[PDB]
Structure formats: C-alpha cells, structure tokens
Image (cartoon, rainbow over all chains, first blue to last red; front, side):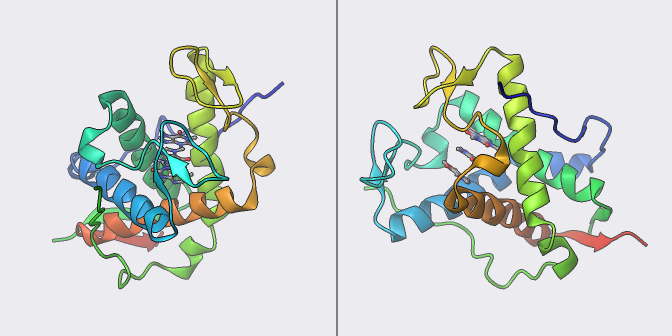
Length: 94
Length: 94
Ligand SMILES: Cn1c(=O)c2c(ncn2C)n(C)c1=O
Ligand SMILES: Cn1c(=O)c2c(ncn2C)n(C)c1=O
Ligand SMILES: Cn1c(=O)c2c(ncn2C)n(C)c1=O
C-alpha cells in the first residue's frame, strides 16, 4: 500500500513572469526528452513498451492532449518550487 | 515523421550544489505527482490507463529502476537549465 509523502510546495512562490513561461518550459522539456529517446531508437507506439522501444508520447508537444500538457506544466513548476525550497534564489534578470 | 528540435541547453551551467540535489528534486517531483494522482482515484496498474486511472509509476520513487531515476534527474536538470536560458538567475541563498 503506497502513500506518497511529498514535501509541501503550496506555499512556495515563484515569479509570475516564470509561471507565464511554463508552457514553453514543458514543451522544451518534452522535446529534449523525445530527442534522446529517438536518438537511441525509440519510435511511436500505442503504449509504453521498453523491450521494443515504443512510446505514445513521441509526438510533437503541441499534439498532446491538454490534460497532459497541464500535467507537464505542473511538473515543470513543481521542479522549480523544489529548487527554491532547497534554498536557491529564483529572480528574473534585469 | 516526428523530428524533435529542442532548444540547446548544453552550454547552460548550473551550480554544482544544485546538481548535487538532483535525486532529491526528482524524488519529490515524482512524489507530488503520485499524491495528486492518488487523490484523484488513480491506483497502480501494469500499464497506463487514463479511463480506469491506473499507472505503473505509482510506486515509491526509491523502488523505480535506475534507468528511470536517471531520466528523472536529467529532466529536473533540463527544466532548470531552461529556466536559466529564459533569463532567470538561480543562486544559492545569500
Ligand atoms: C514521456 N516522458 C517520460 O516518460 C519521462 C520524461 N522524463 C522522464 N521520463 C520517464 N519526460 C520529460 C517525458 O516527457
Ligand atoms: C509518471 N509521471 C508522469 O506521467 C508525469 C509527471 N509529470 C507529468 N506527467 C504526465 N511526472 C512527474 C511523473 O512522475
Ligand atoms: C518525471 N517525468 C515523467 O516521469 C513523465 C513526464 N511526462 C510523462 N512522464 C512519465 N514528465 C514531464 C516528467 O517530468
């Protein structure tokens, strides 16, 4: 029986200017991931198949369902919130 | 026909102190996702099923294969490099 105990991020505040770019960050995070898989012989498939190297998320980011892009933008902001929580400043450059 | 064309992050340089925390960031990023999913009725399954909300990655982070932990650390780091290349400063708290 699995019960996740994440560290709480709900009070971590990021620059609005950073949240505004979360779509661009998720797309590129997706693209970097897809390049690596395709460079190692993965191809599009209906379900995740490690033994044959097939994955359904190997399509352009823009063609993903919006619920997935939503998950991906959340993960991108959760990552940076965890950075700030581990004690790093995040500031827009002048 | 899909050819990913990500932005090139190879020359983005992150503080080592932040790279040292890769596994902790990836673990919690995974844990926040699992908590969100389980709160919405998702449970473990052997393959992802959006309609019946089953997902194979709904296990503790520590129990994931090393190959997936590696992909998780690289994406956390790719997310942060993308943040730096969009013009934000990441520095240890002063
Ligand atoms: C589909 N997918 C993954 O499966 C994945 C990932 N990072 C780690 N993993 C496992 N990214 C960015 C991703 O898009
Ligand atoms: C398994 N999984 C996902 O499937 C996922 C995610 N972020 C977005 N997605 C879709 N994270 C962090 C994740 O661990
Ligand atoms: C760690 N991780 C995943 O494991 C993942 C994902 N999209 C799909 N998956 C499975 N993303 C964006 C992700 O960051």
